[PDB]
Length: 217
Length: 230
Ligand code: NA
Ligand code: NA
Image (cartoon, rainbow over all chains, first blue to last red; front, top):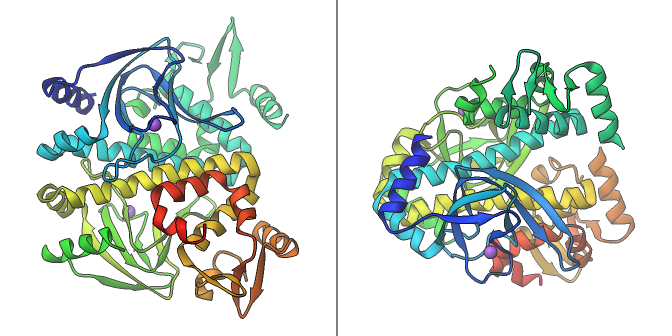
């Protein structure tokens, strides 16, 4: 991704250098008095919120390259009591304190636009997911997630694409033949069934991630 | 507002004039290939999507002042096939083609930040509401929505916290079918009283308990407003 690679250049050029993070560690946490702009260059992460009681809530996932900002750009205060936990074996991320980000984003606006549109993708992503649930119920949510897994972590094979109410819906899917489980691995082969019940999400991939969407279309 | 009125005057310095819209009109629509940046200055609107069926889904409500963009700021292409519909009797909005707004954003940094953190408020808002739904279902969502309106429009009075909201927008939210059941339940439990054609919140703590992460969101995003009713 050129825009992401170009952002990395500008960070490296200004003195910011990548940091390595192991699985399960937090690139930022909900108890830190200081807020950070994270440029996740490689690896997989999840956003979480931990209650007084201690329950973990998984709110969303991010794969690099992407930008996740734990503080408002102006006031520099938290946007929410959230943690950014590495779930891939390792992750590469640039950790910028938010008061410094406002300095380098001032000089150049092209870079600023790249961070700006990552927020836009997040906003439209949530709207697309909400739209699908509110029509096809839990069927839309699960096919939405499967289509997400199929677009990002998919690998085509000649047979297949390789990777409670919920349990019943999954059972229907295998029965309907949309997804096939063979030889210790899971394979999708009716991509357009997922698209019918997660239509807005498919639209979002097309308009937001056309290179990713185009690989299997 | 403070940071919004200076954005208004920034746009005016540059020559963009306010346009007025009326209820049921679309400020932008999902079939226009030209994408826009909307500075909703006054009024209430809602983001809609039309499905294959033709069924209408309401996705988000926005009040002025706020910024709604139909396209990505750099690529200039659509972020989603959406319509922005006016529901208040009248709405005032500055409509900028995505082409022009980028040159303006470049000139100023402080007004960039303003548009930037309205997106941030929306990102965190969606996660907060997701959280509250995963815990309390549509009761959490409706209490969460009533809590925002309470903070934003709530004037404390002897008869409770009155939600000063014209009924044209109040009857759009379903306060005048799953919403009716929830509203009637809060009435039965005396969380709200409906008098003189307006909602009076009697038990704010009840709303906060069922929408805790939206309460947190609002506190972190507008602490001064959050402070009056708390
Ligand atoms: Na933090
Ligand atoms: Na449009």
